[PDB]
Image (cartoon, coloured by chain):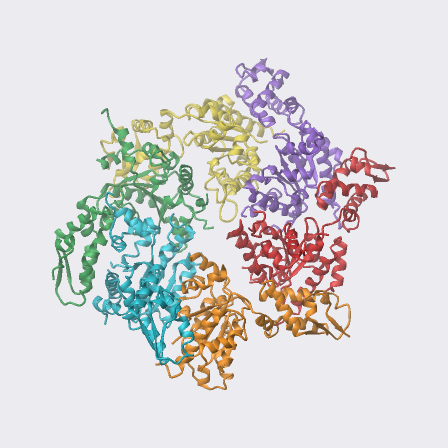
Chain colours: A yellow, B green, C cyan, D orange, E red, F purple
Amino acid sequence: LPTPHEIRNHLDDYVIGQEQAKKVLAVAVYNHYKRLRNGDTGKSNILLIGPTGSGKTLLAETLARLLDVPFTMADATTLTEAGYVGEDVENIIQKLLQKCDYDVQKAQRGIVYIDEIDKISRVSGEGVQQALLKLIEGTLQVDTSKILFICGGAFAGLDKVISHRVSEGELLAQVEPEDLIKFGLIPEFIGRLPVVATLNELSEEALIQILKEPKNALTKQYQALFNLEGVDLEFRDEALDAIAKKAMARKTGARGLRSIVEAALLDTMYDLPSMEDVEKVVIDESVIDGQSEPLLIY
Amino acid sequence: ALPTPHEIRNHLDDYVIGQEQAKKVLAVAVYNHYKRLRNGDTSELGKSNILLIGPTGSGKTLLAETLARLLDVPFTMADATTLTGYVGEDVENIIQKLLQKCDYDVQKAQRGIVYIDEIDKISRKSDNPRDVSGEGVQQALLKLIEGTFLQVDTSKILFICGGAFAGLDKVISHRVETGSSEGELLAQVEPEDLIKFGLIPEFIGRLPVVATLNELSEEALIQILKEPKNALTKQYQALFNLEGVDLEFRDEALDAIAKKAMARKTGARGLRSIVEAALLDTMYDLPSMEDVEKVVIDESVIDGQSEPLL
Amino acid sequence: ALPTPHEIRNHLDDYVIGQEQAKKVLAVAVYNHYKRLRNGDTSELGKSNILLIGPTGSGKTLLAETLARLLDVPFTMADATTLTGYVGEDVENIIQKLLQKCDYDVQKAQRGIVYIDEIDKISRKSDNPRDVSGEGVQQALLKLIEGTFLQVDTSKILFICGGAFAGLDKVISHRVETGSDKASEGELLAQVEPEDLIKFGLIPEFIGRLPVVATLNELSEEALIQILKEPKNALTKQYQALFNLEGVDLEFRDEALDAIAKKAMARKTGARGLRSIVEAALLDTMYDLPSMEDVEKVVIDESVIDGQSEPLLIY
Amino acid sequence: LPTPHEIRNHLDDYVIGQEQAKKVLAVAVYNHYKRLRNGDTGKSNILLIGPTGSGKTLLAETLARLLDVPFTMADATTLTEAGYVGEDVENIIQKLLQKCDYDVQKAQRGIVYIDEIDKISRNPSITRDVSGEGVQQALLKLIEGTLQVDTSKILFICGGAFAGLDKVISHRVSEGELLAQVEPEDLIKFGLIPEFIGRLPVVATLNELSEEALIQILKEPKNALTKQYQALFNLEGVDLEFRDEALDAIAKKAMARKTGARGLRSIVEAALLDTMYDLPSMEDVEKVVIDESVIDGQSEPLLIY
Amino acid sequence: ALPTPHEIRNHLDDYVIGQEQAKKVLAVAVYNHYKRLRNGDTSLGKSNILLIGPTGSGKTLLAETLARLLDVPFTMADATTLTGYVGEDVENIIQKLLQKCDYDVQKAQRGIVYIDEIDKISRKSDNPRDVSGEGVQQALLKLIEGTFLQVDTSKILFICGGAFAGLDKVISHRVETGSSEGELLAQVEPEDLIKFGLIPEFIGRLPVVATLNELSEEALIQILKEPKNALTKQYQALFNLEGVDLEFRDEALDAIAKKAMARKTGARGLRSIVEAALLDTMYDLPSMEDVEKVVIDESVIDGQSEPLLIY
Amino acid sequence: ALPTPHEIRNHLDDYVIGQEQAKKVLAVAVYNHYKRLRNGDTSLGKSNILLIGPTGSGKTLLAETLARLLDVPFTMADATTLTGYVGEDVENIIQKLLQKCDYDVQKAQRGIVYIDEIDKISRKRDVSGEGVQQALLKLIEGTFLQVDTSKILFICGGAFAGLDKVISHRVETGSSEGELLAQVEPEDLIKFGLIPEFIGRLPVVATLNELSEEALIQILKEPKNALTKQYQALFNLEGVDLEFRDEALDAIAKKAMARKTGARGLRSIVEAALLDTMYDLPSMEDVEKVVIDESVIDGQSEPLLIY
């Protein structure tokens, strides 16, 4: 079992900065699996509070991979309706099992990430907290008490509440279950999330990492898109850096990256299904200046 | 069988005059959107939601409507002004209405297109000074953009938000400036510019595709009267045609109509009302006559005194 | 054999006084509408739906009704106010009723004309402040305008939506104005534009379904008088007929007729308020008429305006 | 032919007050039969708008009798279903003929009263009962002329309370003065189709209730309070007798409280409560209610053994 | 086989203390109501009731007891929760009645519905929303008459209760002449409710009017003893399944009554008092081994001394 | 076999610090409630409870502990989220109770329901708040789950900030908070904002003492699941002994007060103080770690490490 040191060390190679949060997660994760090992003798669940594109999703995946443990994501926005009939919640446990080959144990060790938790707080989101709480609370048959839950969120209005209860970065550090309660989260749900981590920083080296690292990264998306056409899309590292610069110069952020990449591939994607070639290559000149069109290989 | 973005733009040229760039943008945005829907499969993909930015009476609404028709897809219009708590339950009204025109079919509703007008109006900023309620809508409608007793998911449906953004031109200039036309500036538009304008970051990040329209030229109006497959001249020539009469519009008359429209600042929206009044007397005594063709000159339009040639 | 707009308007002149422009518009709109139906063939064609805009008691309803009669076509009236979810299934009620009067005939129902009154009432706006329900009707009835177990299609049927639009005059002015006002209100309703109806409370998609826009002008004091005399079924002629089968001659002094017109204008009911005025003025007379044995009754100004002095009785 | 003076004059002996409505009806009726006489050369139909127990029904009957003209009533509520098969409407024309000895002319002069019109105007929830909006049509097919008899000649009088009408008219811009300003528009917005209202040119109004009617409502109707209570007491084997003076006292009580027709029951009940309470405990032939048991409640009803 | 008004009142005497007149009234109203339903035939009285009495007089109890005594589905509702969308919440009273009714339409027709705080929705200058309140009087009015349950509310009996604090004043202003409280609630007339805030058409739907008299201070003691489910009987039963006999001295019962009156909570405040007085006893009760516990005045009023313990 | 009030209170002393009187009260109320349920028979007390104490006094904890001590389904709700459509959201409390109850109707009847911030809905929007007092009042009595809420025990908590003032204005004669909350009467809650019929449904009234800094220390040590014991256990399965110096424990309590988070803020403080230590713990090889004041308050110095 990896030490909290080893864990954080493997977290630095995937996400730049956030030293404090990487500590909290390391200990939270370590203790969790340290409690599962050697038997019980039980909730070290985590609450990631960081802006969108802070690396929340990326961190979760990394933790799962470095532990060689089944992982699965879920959106509080999609779980809102909880399905017209039944519980859309039990669905993610089935996905975790599918990625697990249906091995009850391997699944109980699994990690689950629920994004946009700050969204549900006021199907009514207040009822979603309960549907998601029925999950966290242990129920072919699998108890969820053993699986580690990580709930990510931006919590836009949280900084205000905490600043009232008595800049933004230092404020979030003083977060307390009370703040989350007054935010919209029920006391019962917060009680299931003892651990609370925070993220407050983004870098160019981070933007470039977000562009390729995440299993759900822009580059991977567009590549899949171009791939449907039978075309291979190649992003020169220089192009990725140029993209990062553009994003910074416009102080857009992580969500701002897509608008840049799209504007660089727009024309290409426009008149591509009308021609036949093996692959296309994006150079930094196609991005930073948009002077030249992407390379075409037939 | 989906139409290539080439084909989409081609048909858009039939209902819309100018805005070639905006039409190229929409052509791709649309193609990719439904291309994604038809071949949907786990792993990431863009929302492909659009943000129309152009002067009043430029063709923002028309483009949206035409797009729907060209794709035989349910279409519904909404105004962001009518939205700015109980309206949070009125935002889903946009959905039930889409279902209404969708034969109450959930899947075809997912194909639907929704156009929100006057988005720039709900922007909370010092310019043109309620802010709290307005932002509440940006975030409430924001929940829709993502996608959540219809049971329909708004993730599948394409969102097209239009707005004139009168002040956007000024802020973009204050940014692009260096040391010491509008269309050229609306091209340098960036998310941070919309930020300072009044739109929240999380909302803008949901509208990746940004199309920009150029104000219709005086000359363009004339094209609007002729070129479009449903051009006024073509509509009235058809009317006069099932009467056994040929209707001829002299270029001097068409330009005359365009000028009348500009003096009224009604753009293309004021075209019909002008043409109607000019052919009003003619159509009254048309079925009572027995001639070959009627010719509309300038004197019939501008002066509105002389009668059309018979 | 369809009647030319000339013939249509000519006959409208027999049942309606004034509104010559509106009548020319309707004449053309109507002619084209049925001209399109009879020679219907694939390829574009205007819906030709109409939007009547005039003061109360100007003749909006009368025009619609007369149009139907002049074209021997089924006609049904509806009020947009009674409409403002379950009413969505009450909008189709307008159809079943049209079928009722149509001998239940689907094709002749397609020929039918539907007049919706008080459309300006359902407009959602800050002026005269439910909005959500009202707009819902604008859009619900909007589905009809386009055209969709009668099996009838409402695409064929002509829609005539009337309204007074009390505030429309103000907004149009706030637009047409230049620098620092037009002579007559009717002069403004002429400069009317779809965008003016937009700001008023009507949704764009709805207005776009009413291409033809007709505007009525308030009847003049003298015009009201003509309505009391000239028409074949003029009030005076109707009451003279009533008094006639009593063996009595009814005379309306011009001072009395103008008196009635003025009473009507003060009530802003236009011609619609004419009868109610005449009735009240002849109420007492008609009550003790059959008990008498005189030659003729003469209505002076003092009987109408005053409403106190009794009509002259000539034995 | 009776003059409007003579007509209203004969209406004062059957109904107290309502001078305005008696005028309107006098002229409406007179003109109607004056148009039938001497031939045509045609709709003077009336719409009675008054509270239940205002005397609407009484006025109609009175008008028919004073003219010696066949008369027949009908309930919009009963005509709702319009019969499972056929038209329950044509039925009332047959009744008018039966009371007429089947003389086509005498029948065409006849008067017909349709009560509870305000009821037919409109979630249907797949209800078996026929829609009132459709009833307006079935009833309109009637008003509009059709062994064979044309209805165009018979005078139709439609009575109703129109509870919600006063609101509509107060919005369009107390209750007594409001109803006077009634207009076909108000009735349209109420629920009545324009085509139906167009057949009812004349509109009369009643603001006060009538004791002469209250007393009549107490006994005349087939479901009158007296008849019902008698059936109740009858189950006990007891005969209930309502003294005429008692019925009048009851009417007074109702008027003094401005309750209305529906208010009568609360009065009668309060007068028979004790009796009905301790009646199944004793055995007697009949009970009799005097005006003293009602107007004062001083003494208990009489018991006959 | 329906019970005579005599039998109905007799059983009401078992669950309810006092209110003999109101119970006579309800006895007839009820009997007649169901007598009409069972032998229903064309060519009758709604027989709907209007309860008028002070708070904690027995208005609710009477209604509930009536239902039980007739094995008929019963549902409670409040006019305050009602005062457009609530128009569709009025039919909620029906679906709930059907719920407790095994979803049987006919049994639902037999059901009894009690609406509390009717005097609250009355639109008047006294205690000054009016438009919404009146809207409910008329909305619920539609129910009283009777109209996807498919059930008709004509069959179901409606019992509307209320304290009518101001009603006493107006009745006085009318009955006055020249220059107990229950004596005035007896002279109550429909026109008095009119001036109070109720609409004529609504009042005309409640022909039966019952009036309750505020329970006497002395009656409180009876309430603690006589009722079949009297507090003393409830706690004696509790102490009984512990092998202990619980004795309430009369000095203690009167003491409790007085405590309740000083708190102006009437009978509603009885339980809270008794509980507090027996709290410590019940705590260390299962840990003892005595014969009986005797509650004296000192244990209640003083609340200092402990109850007597007989080994 | 039901536990005597003595046994119930004894176990409560393990999870809760202080509040001995309230625990005696709850011990009796609880015992009687289920004593009534198990031996239920015609011809009894509702036994519903009303917790009144300052914020973070242990109102919620007591409720939760009671449930655990009786292996009975437990669900929490907030009266604030309640204050027409919420009338159908009141039954939501029930369906949730059923959720945790394995969807068993009978065991749901055994369930315990805690409503927090009851003093908040007291009408002294007002119309809506009262509507809830009454809507929830229908529950207290007991009515497609088919479950009857008569059987389930209701525990309503509240701080009642103003209640102290009104009680004083009454108990006064002529010319501590705990001493006054003892003299609490239903009429005092009446004037506060609660309706008579609602209060009459909460016969059992428990009162909690104001939070004391000194007690916080006991909360860190005494409880069977005390933070120190939890962390010592964590450090124990690492082969390390965790020692909390009294100067360190008092330090944590003071930190908690300055933040006015009472006991709820204890963990967050301890975590942050042991964060770095737990991070580089499994990478060391020492005998025990000693937490002094300097590690907590200053938060600068590291904990003592004895090899």
Asked if residue D44 shows in the view, the reply is no
Q: In this view, does B178 lie above or below C268?
A: above
Where in the figure is residue D245, as x and y percent of width and height? 66, 73
Q: In this view, does A189 lie above or below C25?
A: above
Taking depth in this image into account, of A222 and D164 the one nearest to the observer is D164
Where in the figure is residue E125, as x and y percent of width and height? 56, 49
- Quarter containing the C terminus of chain C: bottom left
Taking depth in this image into account, of B37 and B10 the one nearest to the observer is B10
Where in the figure is residue F1, as x and y percent of width and height? 75, 40
Where in the figure is residue B15, as x and y percent of width and height? 24, 50
- Quarter containing the N terminus of chain C: bottom left
Side (left or right) of F79 relative to C213: right
Q: Place residue F51 in its image quadrant.
A: top right
Asked if residue D291 shows in the view, the reply is yes
The structure residue drawn at horizontal position 45% and vertical position 71%, both measured from the top left corner, is D24
Q: Place residue B199 in its image quadrant.
A: top left
Taking depth in this image into account, of D122 and F81 the one nearest to the observer is D122
Q: Is residue D107 above or below residue A153?
A: below
Side (left or right) of F138 relative to A219: right
Side (left or right) of F52 relative to D39: right
The structure residue drawn at horizontal position 26% and vertical position 36%, both measured from the top left corner, is B186
